[PDB]
Length: 106
Length: 165
Length: 54
Image 1 (cartoon, rainbow over the protein chains, first blue to last red):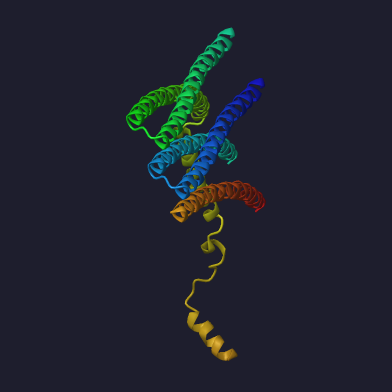
Image 2: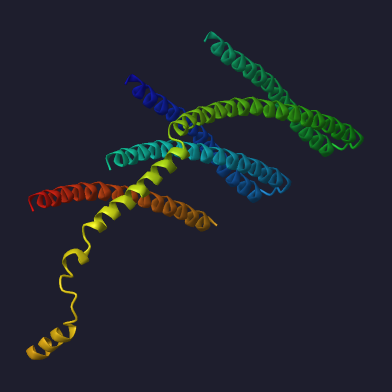
């Protein structure tokens, strides 16, 4: 009876939490990409201005930004995979219940 | 309950302390850079005015200023790394809690409809398909009705076809 | 390399599409089984009535 609504609420809350966390991770990835583009343009500008050890520092900064971007991207992908697992499990349970109903009738 | 707000307050206070200390270190680095630029310009000016042992003293002064600047810069970088560690740890803990919530939900769903129940349902479907095929084949057998005369008039109907042709 | 990622994405989408298509086909087969069983039961009852009369 009332337990079905509670189960639906729990699934919706879990999906909301996972999507909110994925929103934070996408925001952080966007910030990292912004910083990486800024850093690439800055490195090109100062190489225009004639410095190369500073360009080594700039490319190191871009490399660490790219590494952090890749890590947050993979974490967001894993959260997406778990959201997909929740949806697939709900659909599979409903399909199995329908098949069981048809089997009972036949 | 109330402990969560206390934890948030403690993390915010720690970040405030670290950022304030980094502000002092950046201020000191700025002062050192100011002094180093002043010293370089002064050295060039007095070399214009013709003195070189004083220029050795001036370049020594600039060298020690540069060394202090490098040290404070590295200290500020380390403080930045620790601020990053605090933020990364908070984000990682929140992500792990979200993943645990999703795992709990999927575990309850898989407990409700296991794979054993799925295989039982599909076995029932295949068995009922077999039974329905048996019943449908019983009622549609041509040997009950269609084959009334099994007699060897295949030759005779061949002759009637020849008659028509 | 982005095209490798894109074709991988299309491949996983195609796999999921195939799986849902097969599940829908199985549900169609079970609907057909329900209809066939109802028709067969009605036919057997009619044949039994005729057999009683004869």
